Amino acid sequence: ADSVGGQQVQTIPMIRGARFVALFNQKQPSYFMNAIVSLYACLNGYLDDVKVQYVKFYEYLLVHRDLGIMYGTAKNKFFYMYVQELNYLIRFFTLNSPILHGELEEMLKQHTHLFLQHYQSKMNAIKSEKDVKALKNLLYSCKRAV
Amino acid sequence: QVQTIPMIRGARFVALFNQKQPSYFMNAIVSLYACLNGYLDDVKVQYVKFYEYLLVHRDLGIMYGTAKNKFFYMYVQELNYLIRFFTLNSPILHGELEEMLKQHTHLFLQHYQSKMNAIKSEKDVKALKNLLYSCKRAV
Amino acid sequence: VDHYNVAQDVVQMLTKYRELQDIIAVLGIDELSEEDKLIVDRARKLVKFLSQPFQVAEVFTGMTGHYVQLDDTIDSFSGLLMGTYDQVPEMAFYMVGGINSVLEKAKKMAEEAAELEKMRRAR
Amino acid sequence: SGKLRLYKEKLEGYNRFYSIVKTIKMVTLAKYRAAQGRIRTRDFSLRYTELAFSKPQASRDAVVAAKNALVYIPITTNRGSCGALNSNIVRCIDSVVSSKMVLMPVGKRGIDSFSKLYPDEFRYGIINDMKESMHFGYATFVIENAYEVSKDADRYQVIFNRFVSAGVQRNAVYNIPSYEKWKEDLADAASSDNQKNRYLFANALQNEEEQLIRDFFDFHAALAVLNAVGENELSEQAARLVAVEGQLTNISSLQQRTSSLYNKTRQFGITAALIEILSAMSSLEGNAMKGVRRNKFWEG
Ligand SMILES: O=c1ccn([C@@H]2O[C@H](COP(=O)(O)OP(=O)(O)OP(=O)(O)O)[C@@H](O)[C@H]2O)c(=O)[nH]1
């Protein structure tokens, strides 16, 4: 409200408020586990290094994919986003609990590292007439996919 | 802040208009005449109510034994109908009016405002504020 | 008459504090004169001193509530406005009732600070 | 209705305007504070410039005596909303109108204000984008353009705004006489007992070469211009805050007035609609007529 006509200052509250506003965009209702995990990841600053345009793609990879398993780096024993039955364990035990807090942080850190290393790096190197359109279509599809 | 003669008298008049109870005709007209003729120019705005209270109720001239008027005193409430008859500018009631106003202003500036301008103690500041509150509510 | 005078003084100080808050937000704290700084400190103490814990909230807040007498409030605010309690820390007025509570909280804060400093010197 | 929505839209627009002006106030205050640092670092660069040019002189003889061009370099802001600075500068210039007056104003507002009022006493103006810090190069550009405007000029009067405090912005003048007149005055001070405060300064200058003296003259003239522009910028930022605060107060008054009108209009509209409906209902009821009752009246 105090930077409408001036260059904004990229402080921590704004760096996370932008992502939070970006995450609220969705077409279909979200399963509780996916939504709470994404909100927790954005709350602890795991999306600080992710551009606001790629937040939806990051969330889609977190939910419907598993970078750790893809690159053979996942070390968690049970906490994986493909285990849809962790929703009730999360509901009974909050994310800020020793049962789930450690593996949750490990998975989020690994996913953020792999994303920044592999996907966003290629996104920032897009220079063509068709790759740009393909990236735009992918981002739009991910916007209404999660 | 340029303060010309009209501004000073206007501020004093606005200060005098602050009232709680209706004022007797003689007191109100005498105070208005004193303010209009520039007798409150040296009096600070915040002390106008105290000055008016001293003029109406108390009598500095009698207190310090420096009174020269024969009849014109604020304690003589009978003068109200004499003032109402001719004017405050009549030659009968003009000389004594000016004399008592000048004496009251001189004594006030010499004794009361001089001391009020030399108050720094927190207790004395509170006492002065209480005095001003009381005066503003009683003439 | 004392009640009315104290109430008017508190209102005037709060209004002046709002004006000074605007000024410092524009220019800065260090630009205020000596009188303005004292007014700001007293007004902040007043704002912190107007809060009170209710006995109804003892179960939830866990701290005993206070029932302040009328004369006690008048005396406390009159003393604060004059400047008698210019040495008490600002936080001593937060969520307390009366003036005795302020003194007790200030003493407890001083004791806690002394104990912490003594422990620090050991290590 | 439409009129109610009209007032609602007007109030929303005023709110948007108020928010934008508040952001402008914040931005201006940021630069006011950011370039407030000058205050600590000023009032020491121009010490021997005083000796070079400070002279208590009458405002008439210095004006009437000269028969060559009198250059004037008023300092004016590019953007409006500063306040009364430009108006006061224009008034000062108007009071000094002469057949010898020549204007090389500074800033877009100064150009646009002195071009129309003084068409035959205006040559061209200088403009600086407020992107970098006011530096020596800008002052040198101004001085070079001033010389080229009138090289045989009796003096070069710079009029600017001095920022005494956050709320005080006075008008100040720097007078820069021609090299010949300055040399004459310097020689008189060095020789005669008069101008005893500049005696050492004048004698020191005379001992040196003439190129050094000319460089000294140009260097200190540029310093004076630099001081003038810096103070004008600071005064403009401060002065600008007053104008922005005035605009905010005006916008708030307009918002209050429009809100009052909106409330009044909606109440009147509701009342009028209800009265119209009730009038229609009463008209319908009145036309109704009670017919003959078909009941056993005798059975009672
Ligand atoms: O033919 C000449 C004569 C004199 N000068 C110049 O006139 C000035 C006379 O200066 P001084 O003779 O008064 O002082 P100085 O010995 O300390 O000289 P510097 O070492 O400071 O230069 C000096 O700055 C000298 O260079 C010339 O440049 N050319």
Image: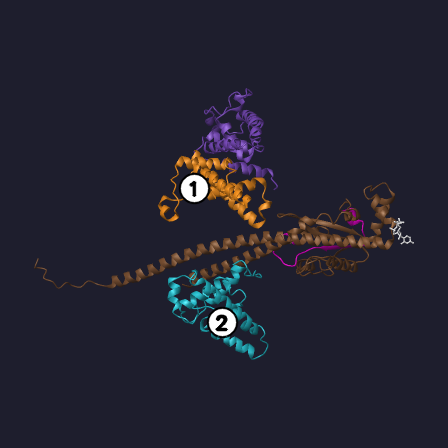
Chain colours: A cyan, B purple, C orange, D brown
Magenta residue check for D67 = yes
Location of mark 1 (residue): C96
Residue C98 lies, in percent from the top left, at 42, 38
Left or right of D216? Residue D226 is left
Residue numbers of the magenta segment: D60-87
The disc labelled 1 sits on which kind of residue? Answer: Val
Left or right of C69? Residue C17 is right
Q: Is residue D186 above or below residue C77?
A: below
**Residue sitting at 81 percent across and 42 percent down?**
D197
**Residue sitting at 13 percent across and 64 percent down?**
D294
Q: Nearer the viewer, residue C113 or D31?
A: C113
Residue extending furthest toward the front: C122
Secondary structure found at label 1 = loop
Visible residue check, residue C27: yes
Q: Quadrant of the N terminus of chain D?
A: bottom left
Q: Nearer the viewer, residue B46 or B61?
A: B46
Left or right of C48? Residue D229 is right
Residue C71 occupies which quadrant of the picture? top left
